[PDB]
Image (cartoon, rainbow over all chains, first blue to last red; front, top):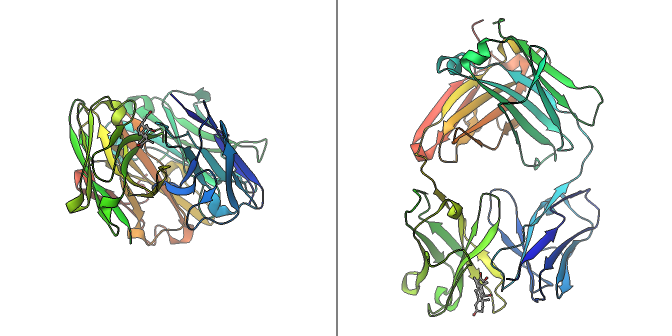
Length: 211
Length: 221
Ligand SMILES: C[C@]12C[C@H](O)[C@H]3[C@@H](CCC4=CC(=O)CC[C@@]43C)[C@@H]1CC[C@@H]2C(=O)CO
């Protein structure tokens, strides 16, 4: 079968930069298409027939290539260009896996906040400790949980937002889910953010035997 | 002008069947080749089915293996996809697509209809207020949250003060936990305004026809 691969899977650039992304075919084909997708909406035809631009596409975009290699290129990139770009061609079952173009911005430390399980959740026998790490950059951030002075790893789920459409920051929730009985056997709960904005973690904590 | 509007997606048990519909407007539907493309939860896009303008020419993607039937009623400007013997791998957003010319770029896409194939049953969310409590904050800003736990399928809609608190909101993508969805939403308001001004998260789960408001009240310590 002829298959497509795309590189890089993810890239970030400041507005104003040149952006190039590549679509490779396992065997020679022609008339490559490129589809743009942003979260929550359908793919949009963007480039087609290797080099034709869809309606509404700025001239800063160009498509090129032949044979086994194709590329999509953007001059002087603008914030609205941020999207995932998928290549596809008329003989291919599976679209290329896409390049996600993200917006580089200044580093920002997260605002960190921690929430004990609600009494309403405790009533049902569950205990989620919620930690928000909001409005930070870059996306790579490390969250550590400590419980009564010892690091805890089981039962942690982390969820990042898509890059924010207004300020290009990321936010993430780190949720520690425990049984009520396991939660009641310990006291100090700490959520620590380690990011590249500082060598020292941002630490938020509480004692269960308060409040 | 041109509109493609899909419908008929939903929850289906493994082994089941579903017909998807795609209502077309604004163009001579019978002059155009049409396709179904699906996007898997991993965001993989797969060419499921193609049908020529007259309905006499058809292609199916490699894993369809005879379980999909594309058809069209040009008199009623509608494209269909019958699906059968559904498997967990068929879970996806299904898009109807129009073709431009004979190099088969897809120049218009519908909004998509979601198809979920699992044994999980529809479950309303539990919603829990997240006040700081023992983790009290003391800056010019306070952050509050709602924990939305235990629902299926996606999606839930979260708003704060009925949408009047729109800035300073972060609603995080849901995650599967015990084979049910959970997400939290955070809101940041000036600390001078809470609790003197009420803060309420509004959670809607249409699939269960549930609406819930949780007022964020300071904890009784
Ligand atoms: C790409 C496919 C093979 C082939 O390329 C098809 C395409 C559908 C459109 C089409 C119509 C034609 O008259 C020429 C072949 C072709 C352009 C097909 C959709 C599914 C199928 C596959 O998934 C094969 O792997």
